[PDB]
Length: 218
Image (tube, rainbow, N blue to C red; front, side):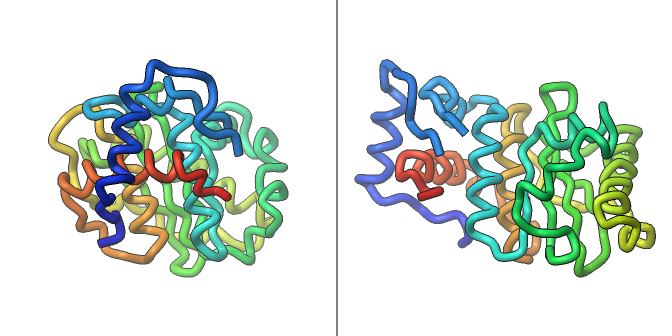
């Protein structure tokens, strides 16, 4: 359900834009080129730009929810809290008012995974559609995200959060990570079980493409 099926007109609009001998803008509300857009074509690794678009979409379509772009985690891990100290303020809310915070993570510029800070359930989750199991990078992500919550909250929350590895549907190929993160973000945003399938994942490409072309961020 959560990932709708496009009608013929809407899908043909995606087709035509993908075949597009291309320009600059498809959107600018985050600047998206047709080149970035083409990353939503089948068999293609999704770039940071597209993931940023989806995170923004989720924010706009989900009350009490912050969904940072992929650069948040880079700055946090490389510069610590001090490197990301204004990011929440730019969201026009305070951490104590939130339900959840989504953090897409691009490990080694190749491997897309997801961090979910659930302030109501008091958990920090690591979600990976290419999971080997708990490893050093996942442990560091969880550590860093807790450190964030501890700092951002002026040391009022986070210290007692459960640091977990969240099972999710696993991908059948080596390039759909970006998409699985989007889906985990959507499903998580709806408090739905992570029980989507690979067929759902294919629809997601067309969905996000549609959202871009319809200027879904108004």
